Image (tube, rainbow over all chains, first blue to last red; front, side, top):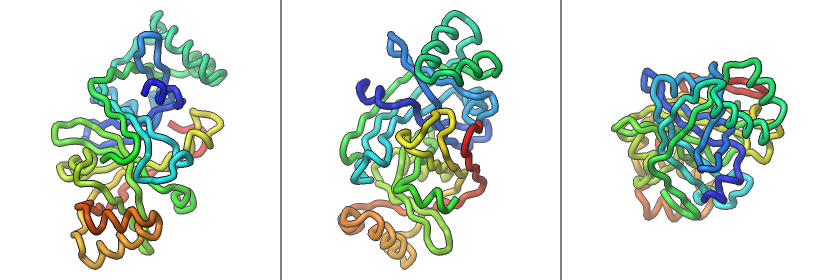
Length: 135
Length: 135
């Protein structure tokens, strides 16, 4: 399944607002040498405001529909995670953003310079991988 | 919305458990003539148990990664919804499951006959469509 994660540029992230309203969105991600997952997200996003209020996040890697012949058997991996804010421009933050820039290119140069985008580490507690039919 | 939604077999659904734990998963869907949205889901699924406890669901339609040139601009549409259970084998239930069978084929024949899958109607209360860059 780490093979599976490598197929993706982004993760689906499910979060909860201060008022208890669930949200689904997506965020580009990287995984470091120690196999930690990080997302890079806008301060304007509902997902980010949710995470700032409630650190619980479900991370889902699900096959594109184009890859899926039987819709009830969509290959997918999901983790229950806890988010932690990595302090802007710490050495760790710059190392992580460097990995984003390596994956995603010039937009990361712009964002890291001009925008207050957040790096969140998503630490997983439990995962589940479904190939074929699974509820 | 309707043109974009027509491109999808399924929706990403984000829910919350009784204990406050978010989940992201997916479910095949239909939209009827009156433009209402429905999911057909297993009684075994975390998403189903969460909906049974907490009838709030975010519904996300997000372009496949394969179709996306710039990962920070994945075309997408999402709705904040409430869920209601459509009573099994009611006229409405049979009409909706017929639509499922028209979309998805023989697997629905099997499930409708043998499995205690639920039909939830998801009524949108707020929505947002993002093409290009948006948080």
